[PDB]
Image (cartoon, rainbow, N blue to C red):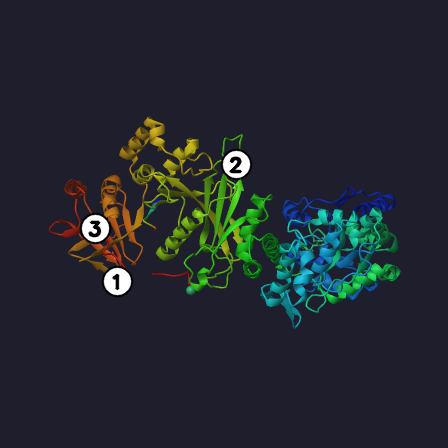
């Protein structure tokens, strides 16, 4: 039982008639006593799903219908249950628009479509074609004016042109959408966007033009035309500009196809006020007086409510709205629409800016829209960088699924301001895409469904100290990441925090002393759930050979902590400074003593290493054994023996090329199948050999590396160090 | 706890 009064929090976009809605709420409060608070937060379509998870979202959310299926699929919307009479009061197509999986998930409010708006004084006869506009602009330019200005930051406004010659979102056939058939990279879409980019190239439009600039331009009479919706008209009236609303220009002898939106009001599933919300929406808003109150503030367009529609249908602006809505298509409401919108937004901005060609932009958008794992990761990125919607990205020209050299399809580069209070410097943040399962169609990775690791289950990241004067992030770390990715795919070994990676060249191909890498959990990036699995984020940390050796001999985690305690060497977020000239040991002499104390008392943390090695003469015992290593692995043999066997621990060399492994074991440890009685044993290519403390000590005495090939022998066994005979191949995760 | 050598 509830002994309390409810309330209503309402979200509506800032370009809509929210004061009129507040007036309808004021009337609701008068009649009912229930307060109604109308808010118009920025990015409310992105915030709503964020806040609903906290339980702090509104009772009612207004938006175009295309977003609501995603919210619904995510369980964020209450099913709406109007009786037949009320359903009868609104047009069937709009109910259709607000229908998801056989349920009504919102109340439809109004039909929106873009139209050509034009200044009758500057232009008494508006152009019937897009092709006319460049010529018209020159004329208007002669007298200090422009032909057309509109919002190029939202793909919504450019889409009518893109769709004109045959661009589409998802193909509608036999009552449903095909989520893999996307029409953004077809000739018609390329043609439309190419036309837009040509308009910008020839200086008839500017790529940076946004909503407010276009609005100011048209409302001050600085531009002859604009493209906008009904909501925009109230402000034009105020400007006292003599304007007309007409059909959008044709492209290639075809009508522009704007996406038709139905302004809809959904009820939060977590709301304790669903009835008050129903009452408000049905009996107060969706009436002549309510919609009139909202429309007076900012025109809604063609309202779903018949009575007010016949009343507003007289308006030739609404007639024009409906002509353009008619010639266009209603937006799908399927969940994949937000990924699709992100994809198209980036393509239009990048093509218009000249950052990318139309072909590359739309190809990425086409692939991008069909890509859930990517969209999940991008989601995390967006959470981290609200300020940077469009990052600089390194894109693989030929993708890995077609056997291009680079397995990371994309590498995003962000500018991270760090924390000046925390003494964390500014730096560039690289994030990779490809080691996880982006697309889930098994082109590169095996798809097993939700839960478990997505692809290898992680993505690589890197933090590079920003140098003074640097306008953009350097791109070499991307190639570095590609190298690491190539290793991961070929070797089949997943990376873990605490691991090290011997590279043996300065990472940036400079003279830098940073020639090696440690791997740790990214300090900011949180693991993500994708339909294809979970993704964690492994940050790369550049180190000196001395530090690598210390990580090997002692442990990686310790060295990482030391690196955190020394800011110029990493700090809390373990940022890499390629120009760093001293090891942490040169910075604090005594610290080395701490490692040395650690090594002698605790030994090495390294369970094993992947290296060039082999062994030779179904569980099998062997009378003789012959072990083979390369120099580097050979240099770790002393670590294996002294560092672990003498501490009652085991050590494993695993070959990356073959399926072989060699595990050194000492007396005890239970788990070993190698007994002193039978020293050498093998489970296939896995070889386990048991060595005694006495023999370990003796072995340590014998080994002092010398020129190759170098040979060691005993009556039972031989040990070779070789010049990389070890040679000749796995692709993908198939 | 693991080492990967000469990944290049
Ligand atoms: O730009 C992509 C954007 O398009 C639509 O948003 C429209 C909205 O429908 C209108 O009511 C008005 O606010 O203009 C918006 C474009 O700025 C989609 O509804 C939306 O999901 C999408 O992000
Ligand atoms: Zn394959």
Q: Position of residue A17 (x, y in %)?
A: 80, 49
Q: Is mark 2 in CB contact (under 8 Å) with mark 3?
A: no
Reading the image, the residue beneath label 1 is: A618
Q: For the residue carrying disc 1, how many other residues have a C-alpha within 10 Å: few (<14), some (14-19), or many (20+)?
A: few
Badge 3, how many Cα within 10 Å: few under 14, some, many 20+? some
Residue under the point 32% across and 39% down = A545
Marks 2 and 3 sit apart, C-alpha to C-alpha, by 54 Å
Residue at x 23% of width, y 51% of height: A629
In the image shown, does B2 or A237 lie closer to the viewer? A237
Residue A726 % position (x, y)? 25, 56
The residue labelled by disc 2 is: A418
Select label 1 or label 2 by which is in front: 2
Looking at marks 2 and 3 on the same chain, the residue that comes earlier in the sequence is marked by 2
Return the disc, 1 or 3, that comes first in the chain's sequence.
Answer: 1
Q: Position of residue A254 (x, y in %)?
A: 71, 68
**A272 or A65, nearer to the observer:** A65
Disc 3: which chain? A
Q: Residues within 10 Å of mark 2 (few under 14, many from 20)?
A: some
Same chain under badges 1 and 3? The reply is yes
- Relative to A4, does residue A60 appear above or below in the rendering? below
Tell me: A625 left or right of A32. left
Q: Which mark is residue A675?
A: 3
Q: Which residue, as the protein is rendered here, is positioned at the far bottom?
A: A174
Callout 2: helix, strand or loop? loop
In the shown orientation, is residue A639 left or right of residue A213?
left
Task: Give percent across and percent down for residue A130.
Answer: 71, 62
Subunit that carries the residue with mark 1: A
Check chain identity for marks 1 and 2: say if they share one. yes
User: Mark 1 and mark 2: span between their CA atoms?
Assistant: 55 Å
């Amino acid at each position: 039982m509830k002994t309390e009064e409810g309330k209503l929090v309402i979200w509506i976009n800032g370009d809509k008639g929210y004061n009129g809605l507040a007036e309808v709420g004021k009337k609701f409060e008068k009649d009912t006593g229930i307060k109604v608070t109308v808010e118009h937060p920025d990015k409310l379509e992105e915030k709503f799903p964020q806040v609903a998870a906290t339980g702090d979202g509104p009772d009612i959310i207004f938006w175009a219908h295309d977003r609501f299926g995603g919210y619904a699929q995510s369980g964020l919307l209450a099913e709406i249950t109007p009786d037949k009479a009320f359903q009868d009061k609104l047009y069937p197509f709009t109910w259709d628009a607000v229908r998801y999986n056989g349920k009504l998930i919102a109340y439809p409010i109004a039909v929106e479509a873009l139209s050509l708006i034009y200044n009758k004084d500057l232009l008494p006869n508006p152009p019937k074609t897009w092709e006319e506009i460049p010529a018209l602009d020159k004329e208007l330019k002669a007298k200090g004016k422009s032909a057309l200005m509109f919002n190029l930051q939202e793909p919504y406004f450019t889409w009518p042109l893109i769709a004109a010659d045959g661009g589409y979102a998802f193909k509608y056939e036999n009552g449903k959408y095909d989520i893999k058939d996307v029409g953004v990279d077809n000739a018609g879409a390329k043609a439309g966007l190419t036309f837009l980019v040509d308009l910008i190239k020839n200086k008839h439009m500017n790529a940076d033009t946004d909503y407010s600039i276009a609005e100011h331009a048209f409302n001050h009479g600085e531009t002859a035309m604009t493209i906008n919706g009904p909501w925009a008209w109230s402000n034009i009236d105020t400007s006292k500009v003599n304007y007309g609303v007409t059909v959008l220009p044709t492209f290639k002898g075809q009508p522009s196809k704007p996406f038709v939106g139905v302004l809809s009001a959904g009820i939060n599933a977590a709301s304790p006020n669903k009835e008050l919300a129903k009452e408000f929406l049905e009996n107060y808003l969706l009436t002549d007086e309510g919609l009139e109150a909202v429309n007076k503030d900012k025109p809604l367009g063609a309202v779903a409510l018949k009575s007010y529609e016949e009343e507003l249908a007289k308006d030739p602006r609404i007639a024009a709205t409906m002509e353009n809505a008619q010639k266009g298509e209603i937006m799908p409401n399927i969940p994949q629409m937000s990924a699709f919108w992100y994809a198209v937004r980036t393509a239009v901005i990048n093509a218009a800016s000249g950052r990318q060609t139309v072909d590359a932009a739309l190809a990425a958008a086409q692939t991008n829209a069909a890509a859930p794992g990517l969209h999940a990761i991008y989601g995390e990125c967006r959470r981290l960088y609200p300020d940077q919607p469009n990052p600089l990205q390194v894109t693989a020209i030929v993708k890995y699924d077609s056997f291009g050299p680079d397995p990371l399809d994309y590498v995003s580069m962000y500018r991270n301001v760090g924390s000046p209070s925390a003494n964390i410097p500014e730096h560039w943040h690289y994030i990779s895409f490809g080691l996880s399962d982006l697309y889930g169609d098994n082109r590169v990775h095996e798809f097993t469904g939700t839960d478990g690791p997505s692809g290898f289950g992680f993505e690589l990241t890197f933090r590079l100290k920003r140098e003074t004067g640097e306008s953009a992030p350097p791109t070499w770390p991307a190639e570095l990441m590609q190298g690491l990715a190539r290793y991961v795919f070929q070797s089949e070994n997943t990376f873990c925090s605490g691991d090290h990676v011997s590279w043996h060249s300065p990472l940036d191909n400079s003279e830098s002393r940073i020639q090696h890498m440690l791997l740790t959990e990214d300090p900011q990036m949180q693991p993500v759930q994708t339909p294809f699995g979970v993704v964690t984020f492994l940050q790369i940390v550049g180190v000196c050979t001395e530090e690598l050796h210390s990580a090997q001999q002692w442990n990686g985690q310790g060295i990482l902590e030391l690196l955190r305690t020394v800011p110029i060497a990493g700090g809390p977020w373990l940022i890499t400074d390629m120009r760093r000239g001293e090891t942490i040991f040169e910075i604090d002499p005594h610290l080395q003593e701490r490692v040395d104390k650690g090594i002698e008392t605790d030994g090495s943390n390294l369970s094993g290493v992947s290296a060039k090695c082999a062994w030779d003469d179904r569980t099998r015992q062997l009378e003789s054994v012959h072990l083979k290593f390369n120099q580097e692995s050979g240099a770790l043999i002393p670590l294996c023996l002294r560092g672990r066997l003498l501490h009652g621990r085991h050590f494993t060399y695993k070959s990356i090329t073959g399926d072989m492994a060699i595990t050194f074991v000492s007396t005890g440890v239970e788990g070993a199948f190698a007994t002193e009685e039978h020293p050498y044993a093998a489970h296939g290519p896995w070889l386990q050999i048991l060595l005694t403390e006495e023999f370990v000590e003796k072995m340590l005495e014998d080994l002092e590396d010398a020129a190759l090939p170098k040979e060691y022998s005993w009556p039972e066994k031989k040990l070779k160090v070789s010049i990389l005979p070890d040679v000749v191949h796995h692709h993908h995760h198939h | 706890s693991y080492g990967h050598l000469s990944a290049s």
